[PDB]
Image 1 (tube, one colour):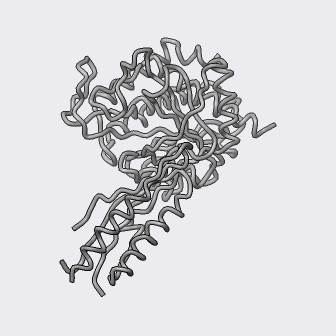
Image 2 (image 1 turned 30 degrees about the vertical axis):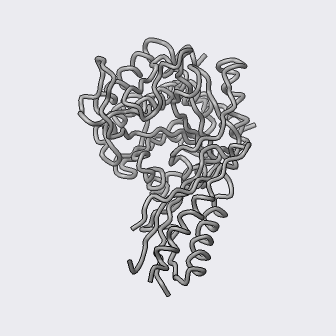
Image 3 (image 1 turned 180 degrees about the vertical axis):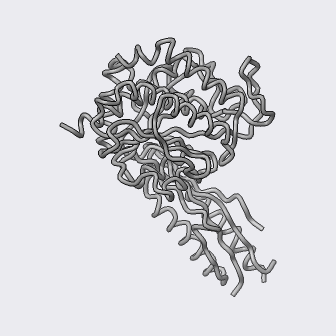
Length: 375
């Protein structure tokens, strides 16, 4: 029944106005002042006790008994420094900033889920923790909330991401590794006279050789050299893998090291340069995935769940999912003729008719998780 509640004028109209208010006033990482104030106003109106501030602008709400088991639902708050190209009534009023990744929709659907869960709060066998996360785009926000104790005593966390790659109203996931990890590296190459330059060009080519694509998408490995700048040469770049992420880091370091040595050079390799720690692959807990497929099929029909392919994208939800059982899913918006622009596009649109689906999926997943836990 919560789908029909999610679609009702009361809830749907309210979600649309919230979404559009955020959309008109996009804020970047750690600067989500107005977005944070709106979330907190709505929690108060529902109402729902919360902790604030968490990671400057972040907010954590609670619904249910107030006691364990705690299950978390997550939305991200931040926009991107992109000029909106969509001409419409609720276009960004802030030039050069836009919600081009659906994050306005994510906050809204989580507030929708909070409204829905609150109506059933006395039946929840535990507590739903609503995590409104700042600064996803710079990949530091989830990590900062984790540092500040956002996951303490939390047994599971679920996140939804709106997608133009999945058809409207379908939800997509897969068990295990889902989104690729990402790391950076910096190496300094020094002679033990042309040897450092020779060593560097050799290193650059040997590293470019570690890019591997095969027939299983999870095997894909990317190593990029983005920086090279003669007494010493500094090489920097990035690496990505769905699996064997640590082994790829070690292989990058081994290549730099061995190549420098055979060119009579020293090499200093840093795999966390300037405190840039790697972000691990986003792994969907198998038990949570199984629960999610059943939730989605019960709520929206057998055909509504689609198995997602691995994605080489950037999503800091990985930091939550590395520390507790995590589940990250895609919620489709795409129409039959591919009219919805990709994430990050200046032409990105949310199909607002999706908002009730995400609200219901969030709510249902929380309820079922707690129910199953009790059984």
